Amino acid sequence: SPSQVRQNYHQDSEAAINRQINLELYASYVYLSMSYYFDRDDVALKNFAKYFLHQSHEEREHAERLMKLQNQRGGRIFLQDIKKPDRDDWENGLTAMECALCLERSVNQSLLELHKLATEKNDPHLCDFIETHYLNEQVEAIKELGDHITNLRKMGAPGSGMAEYLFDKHTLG
Amino acid sequence: SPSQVRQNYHQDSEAAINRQINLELYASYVYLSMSYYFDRDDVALKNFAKYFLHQSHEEREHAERLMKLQNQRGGRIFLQDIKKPDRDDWENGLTAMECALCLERSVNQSLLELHKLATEKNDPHLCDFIETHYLNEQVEAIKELGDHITNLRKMGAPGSGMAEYLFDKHTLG
Amino acid sequence: SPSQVRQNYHQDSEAAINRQINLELYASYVYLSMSYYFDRDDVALKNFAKYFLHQSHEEREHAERLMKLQNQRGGRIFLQDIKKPDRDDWENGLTAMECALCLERSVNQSLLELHKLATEKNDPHLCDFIETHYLNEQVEAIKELGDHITNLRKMGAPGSGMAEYLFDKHTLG
Amino acid sequence: SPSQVRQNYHQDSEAAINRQINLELYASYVYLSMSYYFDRDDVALKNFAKYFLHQSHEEREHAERLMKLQNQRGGRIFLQDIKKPDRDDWENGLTAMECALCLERSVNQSLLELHKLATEKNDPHLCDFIETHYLNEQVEAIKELGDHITNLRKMGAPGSGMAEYLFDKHTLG
Amino acid sequence: SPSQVRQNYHQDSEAAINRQINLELYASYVYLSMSYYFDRDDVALKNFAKYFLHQSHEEREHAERLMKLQNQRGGRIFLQDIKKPDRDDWENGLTAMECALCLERSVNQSLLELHKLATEKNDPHLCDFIETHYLNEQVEAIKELGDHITNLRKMGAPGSGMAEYLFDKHTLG
Amino acid sequence: SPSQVRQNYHQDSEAAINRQINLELYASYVYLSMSYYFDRDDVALKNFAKYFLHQSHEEREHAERLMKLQNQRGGRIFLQDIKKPDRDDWENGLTAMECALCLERSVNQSLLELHKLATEKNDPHLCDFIETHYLNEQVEAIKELGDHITNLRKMGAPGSGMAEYLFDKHTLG
Ligand SMILES: [Fe+3]
Ligand SMILES: [Fe+3]
Ligand SMILES: [Fe+3]
Ligand SMILES: [Fe+3]
Ligand SMILES: [Fe+3]
Ligand SMILES: [Fe+3]
């Protein structure tokens, strides 16, 4: 039953990899929702839409990389239902940035739990994979989101639409 | 009397094409009026003037394409008087954008009526011509105008001239 | 309440566009499942994996284009849950090709129903959009899948793994 | 019995596609006859021969495209006898142009009937195919033939051979 | 009320500039009418159509330059109705050339009256503008039209259609 | 009645040239039938379709060259009805190759009879034309078809579809 390539790969690690795949695709779905929310005629923030579409594409790559890692170690991929994003209307740019920050913090927390599980199971390859491809990216993404939120708050968002317009033109542009 | 190239071309379709030609040229005239209104020394919005001059040139092309289609199908072009635009002073940028949105919606409504007439008369070539060259352009133009109006409203226009200046420099520039 | 860009866009058309978006993303999910099924060490068909990953990326683009069309016409995007693919193990290459053919036929049937609804609602722009971007692509994809299935059956698949190997190397390679 | 790719493709549409294929090849045969009639030593109009040979090649492509469409939709091609052109001697350039105009009008009428049948059978892909690849081409070809006939009549053809010589050298050259 | 840039600009000069703008656009409309008259299948003179379309585009530029001059001097543009051309059928090439000559002579006469008014009002900038951008162009256009009419008369137009065909091919081509 | 260029050109030679033209076009029609038979979804042999389409184009050129030769020698072209191919379903690749071999042998036999007639009528130009443009081509085509048939038989065709697939990919590809 076990694959000819499976070595030092625990069942719990495989299940955690599958759950992380589902999370990464949920995050991609949420970012797509934000991106096409900012493409609305009553919102009209092109650079916000570009930023969130790029985030969605990145998360899909993260998930595809996770699926490739699952296949490499001899595990079996079990896809689940990709849940809808918790919101349909994202209010404005600052709220979308804060929701994206909350997402990334959750993805990073899940990745930290996965690394802790791999360390407990003595899987050095999985730990190195998580450290190389997912940890520093999460901290850079969280730092970037925090910078964006700080700039939006200081410019006067969300009360002033001039602030969101100028942030769209200068920072994200 | 009928031309050697006229085939499956109804009289009502020819009359509707002539009326659409007159509308497209009226729209070009209105856009020219807006463009050279924004060139005034007491207005001084160069990018608004460029945008509306480009819209005027586009509408002329639309009309010239309509005249070419009329000649291709064996119909006869009957030009009418190009009426003056309903306004001489366009108040400000937001009002001009809203008036342009109203125009385009009317041109699109006229184009939809023309397509409905062509479908009722079983003229597939005319329907395909309208769909290919005029429908998607109208929806893109209307979407762009809606985005511009939303951005202008959110920036604080027309109350704040800083908003119109920054929209001129960043969006239309 | 209605957007400033909404014109000749029916509620039923908006709902059908949302359902088509959900279908296109389900199809992308299914193609991703097939692609990373063929990346398994006990399957090892690299070109099948490439083909299905490309199909998944294409379907996402189809969905993103549908979302853009929804935003252009003044409709509102309502995302739903992306259901898991009906299978986790795809047996072999021929079975995967047949399942992909069944999917595409369903997507084409849904697109034909959407076009019929748009024609009944007299929405020429939506009909032209569906015809230009989705109908001929569906027929080309279905034709390609039928060719692949015929070649696989004639080569001796799925009984002979030599047939699947040679089809992977020569056709999909 | 039905092909694995056949979907929303009616039998009447398949028969009409076969008849259109036969017509397109008959038109190609007629154009070839005209072209090699103008290559005679007692006619000696090289540019007329080039024009009609190009028309023949175009019609063959039209037929080959029709055959490809028939194969794409799951229909079966049934070739018939290609009838000889109704004339062996084409009198002169103006008569050949008028006969070519009559042909094209017939091909366009057949294409319009085919589009009407496809619309009645609710085959949007076939309607879009006919509109995209065959309707506007027919109207451009008919317009070009009408222009050529008008120029030939005004120059003094067919009474004056100087007119046909100058039309061959300047227009078709 | 007067603009901050208005200096040595008389009200009569502003009114004459507005009337000249309306004339230049009427001339552009007339040239467009001629150009798309020569695109008819029963006329079929491509180079005449090109010539008159170029004349129409030039006259629009003349009008746009006049509007720019009006804005530069502090005057206010007041657009009027663009009257339809006096003819729908232009008979033939020679008649169209003669009508174009009559137009240009009228535009030049209006420009000469405008220059006389500016000289009487002691507006050296307006006089220099008219001399630099409009007088020599009118005399060159009138000379070219006279040459075309002389050539058409000598070749045998409008009685001989061979003359119009050869003039279209050689002179305007 | 005879043309000014007719010299040493017999009536029987002219009739044989016309019959050869009709045969060459029938062969082109048959090759087109085979090519678009192999484009079917239940056949799916792209390289067979390419090969037979190229053969059809070549035969048309052969016929056009024959028509040009007929015009050069002062003969008159008399086109006949192009008969439908004897088959609609070509079974498989080997059967199509064998039918193509039978055709070419017939075309070569007809060409040999035409050369014999020209030699009997003492027409050295016609004999040289047939030898230069048609004899060696027939023997090369027959040799190529024999090689293809031998390879198909040795690979196991038509019983093994793997043989036809590999021949399509390697030989015709
Ligand atoms: Fe990620
Ligand atoms: Fe327009
Ligand atoms: Fe798709
Ligand atoms: Fe054709
Ligand atoms: Fe002028
Ligand atoms: Fe041949």
Image (cartoon, coloured by chain):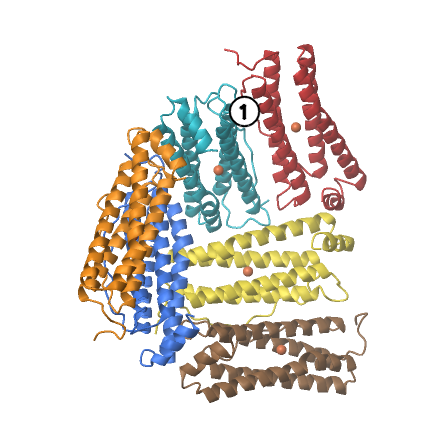
Chain colours: A red, B yellow, C cyan, D blue, E brown, F orange
Please state the chain letter of the residue tagged with numbered disc 1 in the rendered image: A
For image coordinates 65% across by 46% down, the residue present is: A44
- Image quadrant containing the N terminus of chain E: bottom right
Q: Left or right: D145 with respect to B43? A: left
Residue B78 spot, x, y in % from top left: 47, 72
Q: Left or right: C28 with respect to A85? A: left
Residue F90 spot, x, y in % from top left: 26, 39
For image coordinates 58% across by 77% down, the residue present is: E27
For image coordinates 52% across by 65% down, the residue present is: B63
Q: Does residue B87 appear anywhere in the picture?
A: no
Ligand 1 under 8 Å from disc 1 Cβ: no
Crowd band around label 1 with a 10 angstrom C-alpha radius: few (<14), some (14–19), many (20+): some
Q: Does residue A77 appear anywhere in the picture?
A: yes
Where, by quadrant of the figure, is residue C140 drawn?
Answer: top left
Count the labels in the image.
1
Ligand 2's quadrant is: bottom right
Q: Is E126 rendered above or below residue C124? A: below
Q: Secondary structure at mark 1?
A: loop
Q: Amino acid at mark 1?
A: Asp
The residue to which callout 1 is attached is A81
Foreground residue among F36 and F125: F125
Q: Left or right: A127 with respect to B134? A: right
Residue B67 spot, x, y in % from top left: 48, 67
Where, by quadrant of the figure, is residue E161 drawn?
Answer: bottom left
Residue D142 spot, x, y in % from top left: 37, 65
